[PDB]
Image (tube, coloured by chain):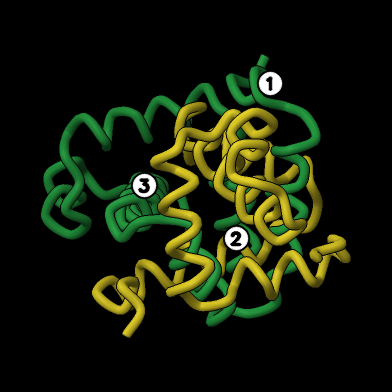
Chain colours: A yellow, B green
């Protein structure tokens, strides 16, 4: 019952298969610069920082100050961590981020 | 002189490092469902479909019909194909999608 189920199909599969072909960090810079605006990329980056910081055990007050994320953004990320796919956990755990 | 240079730094590196840890297509579904809204994901999928179809030699009208994309969206993708990082070329080649 993921919201993304609405979109499941060949085109979305191709986008994800494309992202899987990226092999290093600079390829990601090049690809996401082509694909996305600066504002879009900034938002995605902010969201992951918020998720990381929540998991590290920081107060929401501190998260605002360090990540520059808005309260509305922090709220959305909060909702995803609790009522989502545990995908932030999966990927943060893979990078060996010390979550407390 | 990529626009993304505005954002280059530790947080953005971390987002890309996260994306590089994804191993399969279903993990992408779970991660991007957590990270993004349905509307954001649909937008990104549409852009890649447009890029592919431009590179295959479809005209704007066919692209509008098959991908849902507005002329504005198509225009922006076209601009990025001419003046961007050639990153759509890169990923389309790796997925062995035939292009002109």
Quarter of the figure with residue A32: top right
Q: Nearer the viewer, residue A91 or A98?
A: A98
Which residue is pictured at 58% across the width and 20% down the height? B3
Q: CA distance from mark 1 to mark 3?
A: 21 Å
Q: Quadrant of the C terminus of chain A?
A: bottom right
Q: Is residue A56 visible?
A: yes
Q: Which residue is mark 3?
A: B47
Find residue A81 and report its horizontal and vertical position in percent. Answer: 53, 67
Q: Which residue is mark 2?
A: A19
Q: CA distance from mark 2 to mark 3?
A: 13 Å
Q: Is residue B52 visible?
A: no
Q: Are marks 1 and 2 in contact (CB under 8 Å)?
A: no
* SS state under label 1: helix
Q: Which residue is mark 1?
A: B5
User: Which of pointers 1 and 3 indicates the residue nearer the eye?
Assistant: 1
- Which chain is home to disc 1? B
């Amino acid at each position: 019952s993921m919201q993304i189920e609405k979109l499941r199909g060949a085109a979305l599969d191709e986008l994800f298969d494309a992202i899987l072909t990226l092999e290093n960090r600079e390829e990601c810079y090049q690809f996401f610069d082509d694909l996305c605006t600066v504002n879009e990329i900034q938002s995605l980056s902010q969201r992951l920082q918020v998720a990381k910081m929540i998991k590290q055990g920081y107060t929401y007050a501190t998260i605002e100050q360090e990540s520059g994320a808005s309260t509305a953004t922090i709220s959305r990320v909060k909702r995803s961590l609790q009522w989502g796919n545990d995908a932030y956990t999966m990927i943060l755990d893979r990078m060996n981020i010390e979550t407390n």
